[PDB]
Length: 356
Ligand SMILES: Nc1ncnc2c1ncn2[C@@H]1O[C@H](CSCC[C@H](N)C(=O)O)[C@@H](O)[C@H]1O
Ligand code: SF4
Ligand SMILES: [C-]#N
Ligand SMILES: [Cl-]
Ligand SMILES: [Fe+2]
Image 1 (tube, protein in one colour):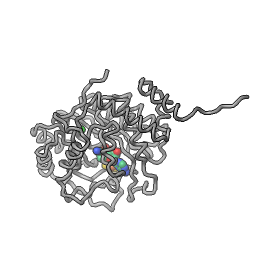
Image 2: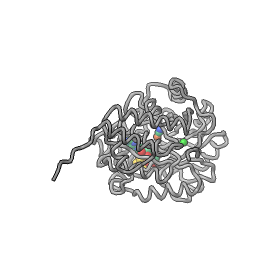
Image 3: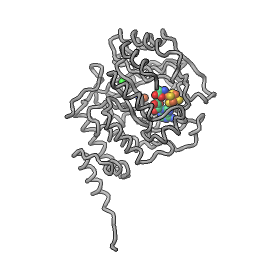
Image 4: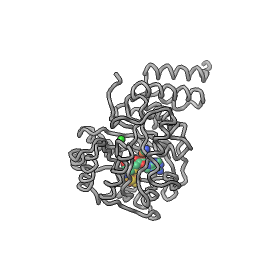
């Protein structure tokens, strides 16, 4: 028997970068990219992702204004502050008039997509959502829904009402962990919803949380390969942020750098996808969204939920700032985009097929 020494780190990193540039996306390559803790490797990975972003989605940063119109949820996900067992949290629902008029104001401020997100709140489902969507589509903008898991019939009604996109983050592709963290449902259900949305012709968004309890680097690799397999139009990635009024209150927070590497690898794997710099990235690090927009992201989703509701959509701590008026976010993100040397989107920013 003979020795078995490891290879030097910088050269291994350079070999990983070469494999990523040649698009040799083996599990071992993705695992090693996620595992290397060298600032200079990571910077090269971010620059690769940024290059691919420049080439295949360009310099426009698309603005998607989010209205979080109800924090009522029938589910009990272990990570989420809106879980039904959290009795500390004041619940609210916006009327259709409040929602439509608030959407009109975002359109006037220049948002070209309105995102309607909520807890899984049966009050609205399906017909109130259809009515709201029809009204917002008259404003000349795209509509994205992010309402959770519903029957195919509901998704079909909302498509006929005019919805363009659906964001249903897959959370984790590990089916054992998924069920542990989402005890009402399953990864199979979540995937069936994503497949139905695609079949109905939505632009479909998935994406995971990074740093969930029990999640490993091998699970993150499976998330990347899941995203690649389905060629999602949008991918929403952010860190898990523990919420004090949930069973996961005392667990580790997701790591910003690891999450940024997931965004970068997602852009490399899916060159023409729409990738937000998520709210959670801005919560975890000051300037986190700006950094993420330099590491492969091309979308920003300012929070347009009005007072007094905004502060109650408490998915995780620190999500909401109440230091400025509730109309500040769209101008703010426009200034951010200008300071980055980017441009706001000129059209609805739908996913295009320009890579291969
Ligand atoms: N503690 C937490 N940390 C980070 N993101 C969280 C979080 N709790 C929830 N989220 C994220 O918030 C997203 C929107 S939840 C609202 C939409 C819908 N009920 C749905 O579940 O799809 C979830 O997809 C999840 O990725
Ligand atoms: S993640 Fe979505 S489904 Fe789960 S508790 Fe939160 S709002 Fe409800
Ligand atoms: C979400 N941004
Ligand atoms: Cl969108
Ligand atoms: Fe988001």
